[PDB]
Length: 265
Length: 264
Ligand SMILES: Fc1cccnc1N[C@H]1CCCOCC1
Ligand SMILES: Fc1cccnc1N[C@H]1CCCOCC1
Picture 1 (cartoon, rainbow over the protein chains, first blue to last red):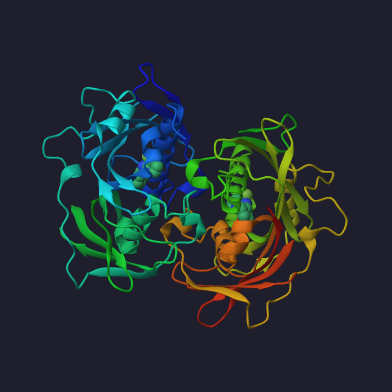
Picture 2 (picture 1 turned 180 degrees about the vertical axis):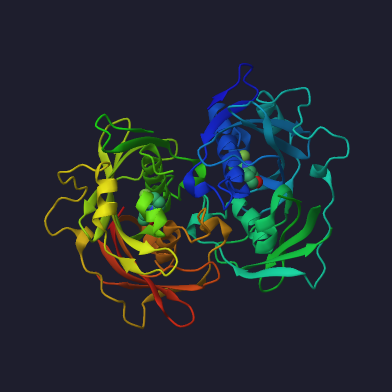
């Protein structure tokens, strides 16, 4: 992988692995999400991070995902080479945004796109906060100054408000728990695990006859290593749409909410 | 990746990813196991198995893992390049064996080694069988003829008999279930998931103060997508553990194993 010529974006190529694919011999949405995370991390590293700035480490602040939005046109097959370009942009004092473009390395065609919203939070108290000028000036030199959006369209799905699923849910998958493979290097549940948990309450027949085109996920609260999660889904819809809710098994505390759009094969 | 000069083994390099590492910023044993599986699949593809041969497909036969043995001296760090060499060998009528050698690409030193036993099975009835000479001759042209062992030493850990853990277990993790990410392209639970499940009953304090040096796992029966598993561990000792994976309900054995851990 490498930063582009202007140093304002990063590209990396990946060869799709045997264990990374599902029944159609194409990459699952969780493999795609893992690759987006890996290219994001390689971009932060190439521009001097170890992505907390100098001022952020001093003040015990971190970037946390508030929303993830992915749209896939074609999932790459086992052994195929996918090229992913990523970049960041400041969204004023609200936080930051990281976008991605997925391309087939052989044809050069766009096969997918993603966008994410990140908010600043104190690592210890979990208290959200706005972005100060001191922090903003430190990461602006690594961002394109003019807007560059993976989802430019005026009324696109990435900025839609997601409602809270009402009980009773049409479908459910109960008692989901993270294992050590689900944790990141800091012992927190990896953000991609939540995507997997949301998808667990979709019936196998839908997965067997449809392809996931779009997923939008809001991150409200994190699941601890010793927490248990319930995954809830209700059909809201040639295309099928679903409303999703992840909540703690006991008290029913919301951890995530989301929507998926699926097209018939 | 590519076959070596003689075409009797395969090498591939991997750059360790951010999500592939644990708390020490080094690859977990499950990442290592995934890489061994990937290089194994790439070897089979390079020699024409787009690893079932022509005769196996007609007779509805597949290779299934009976045992996996891994020894790690150094886990590669996040961003490091690891080189893995793999090869296969016939073990007469019993089945086949696949071995691996892990090396640090920069230093060239051996950082790990692995060996696995595979048995022939009818994919529909799940009935084990011996290897026929028709099948044996079809894969012998892809194997070194003289023995080449990742674990040569006489009386070594890879061939030790593993006993069945007796109730009550010292430690346990119950109600483990596979999710879709745990399944392979054929909708079966990936072999690496069982390694993860075995490790779930090891206490976090042991994981926080020790490094896993050796793991031996016997595969008795598969866990279906709708099955629930209980993971059981007892200290037998460096720290050694005896492991048992069984179905949550009837208590049917799926795996048994042992782990050896060194203090950091
Ligand atoms: F770029 C990242 C660096 C570190 C962590 N996550 C990143 N990106 C997203 C991965 C895909 C699923 O959504 C969550 C976040
Ligand atoms: F070479 C392989 C091809 C396909 C599947 N597994 C392979 N190898 C081992 C993977 C890691 C531990 O489980 C034992 C088998």
